[PDB]
Image (tube, rainbow over all chains, first blue to last red; front, top):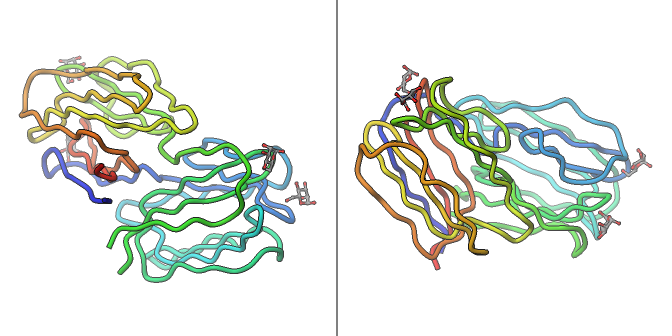
Length: 121
Length: 121
Ligand SMILES: OC[C@H]1O[C@H](O)[C@@H](O)[C@@H](O)[C@@H]1O
Ligand SMILES: OC[C@H]1O[C@H](O)[C@@H](O)[C@@H](O)[C@@H]1O
Ligand SMILES: OC[C@H]1O[C@H](O)[C@@H](O)[C@@H](O)[C@@H]1O
Ligand SMILES: OC[C@H]1O[C@H](O)[C@@H](O)[C@@H](O)[C@@H]1O
């Protein structure tokens, strides 16, 4: 039942509600920072903030996952990369040739889970 | 081609990448504030910030739209309301019995357009 609708005119500079991503990472992802909002704990080391340009979106992803999120790395449609950040635990999963719309999940002292909404090309 | 995939375990507190919404509003929406990130101009009056709780999402929307976004108002699945903020220009459109996933769009000195990704129930 997923879809989208457009409202408004044709002007302005296109933006995404998913506008910037950073992480706190050690052996796991202690937190994911979405638009400067903290989602996780206080451990780990804070990575620099990746800010999407207008029309730039996540196109490729590799996630290492177990009971928590062990590692994350992604690439945008304009050739920019983020990570890999995290450890070697968990199991690997990938998203390829996509347009990531939204990054949700659950977090505590660590980043427990991620729910990525995306268009598959 | 829209879908989603889950990674990780079952712990933690669920969050949304669309975690808070505020607006600058006059006769139009001068800006929409998503997770504290400014999308629009400096005119209008800054509304208070609406922060979603865990498991709370936008379920109903009314948007007044023309060349720009004239007005916005929404209600969550837990009975909370936001707005209406803005003017009486444009034409009215609605989203009903949905779960809003992501709010994108384009902005300049005003909020030009909105692209709402949502699940229709
Ligand atoms: O990522 C989990 C954990 O990994 C390492 O042990 C350190 O960086 C910690 O600070 C961090 O919390
Ligand atoms: O994030 C890992 C872990 O952190 C905290 O201990 C709690 O919030 C747990 O519910 C969560 O699973
Ligand atoms: O919303 C457009 C415009 O509406 C009103 O005229 C005032 O509140 C302005 O400050 C605002 O920029
Ligand atoms: O936001 C309304 C208007 O604001 C500015 O003048 C520019 O960014 C325009 O492209 C945009 O359409």
